[PDB]
Image (cartoon, helix red, strand yellow):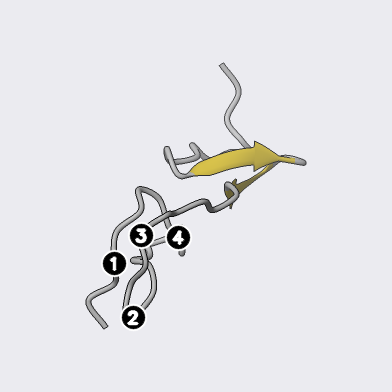
């Protein structure tokens, strides 16, 4: 099928206007250093950052 601007979006991303972008973030956990980011910057699945 089509890629997204030539790329495959990860599970954390959505293809909007032909680019992979992080989907909206909804995490219930409350974390001392905020949420963990993947290598694209997305916060999915929800986990606390190491710091």
- Residue position for label 1: 48
| Observer able to see residue 5 | no
The location of residue 32, given as percent across then percent down, is 31, 80
State which quadrant residue 28 falls in: bottom left
Q: Residues within 10 Å of mark 2 (few under 14, many from 20)?
A: few
Looking at the image, tell me whether mark 1 or mark 4 is earlier in sequence order.
4
Q: How many marks?
A: 4
> Between marks 3 and 4, how big is the CA–CA gap?
21 Å
Looking at the image, tell me whether mark 3 or mark 1 is earlier in sequence order.
3
Which one is in front, 36 or 7?
A: 36
Q: Are marks 3 and 1 in contact (CB under 8 Å)?
A: yes
- Residue position for label 4: 40
Q: Secondary structure at mark 1?
A: loop
Residue placed at 59% from the left, 39% from the top?
14
Q: Secondary structure at mark 3?
A: loop
Residue 39: image tag: none
Name the image quarter holding the C terminus: bottom left
Q: Which label sits in the foreground, 1 or 4?
A: 1
Q: For the view shown, which residue lies furthest in the left direction? A: 50
> Between marks 3 and 2, how big is the CA–CA gap?
11 Å
The location of residue 29, given as percent across then percent down, is 36, 59
Q: Which label sits in the foreground, 2 or 4?
A: 2
- Residue position for label 3: 29
- Residue position for label 2: 33
**Position of residue 18 in the picture relative to residue 13 (left or right):** right
Looking at the image, tell me whether mark 2 or mark 4 is earlier in sequence order.
2
> Between marks 2 and 1, how big is the CA–CA gap?
7 Å
Q: Residues within 10 Å of mark 4 (few under 14, many from 20)?
A: few
Q: Is residue 30 above or below residue 47?
A: below
Looking at the image, tell me whether mark 2 or mark 1 is earlier in sequence order.
2
């Amino acid at each position: 099928g089509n890629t997204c601007g030539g790329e495959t979006c990860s599970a954390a991303q959505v293809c909007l206007k032909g680019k992979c972008v992080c989907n909206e973030v909804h995490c219930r956990i409350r974390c001392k250093y905020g949420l963990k980011k993947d290598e694209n910057g997305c916060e999915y699945p929800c986990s606390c950052a190491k710091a």
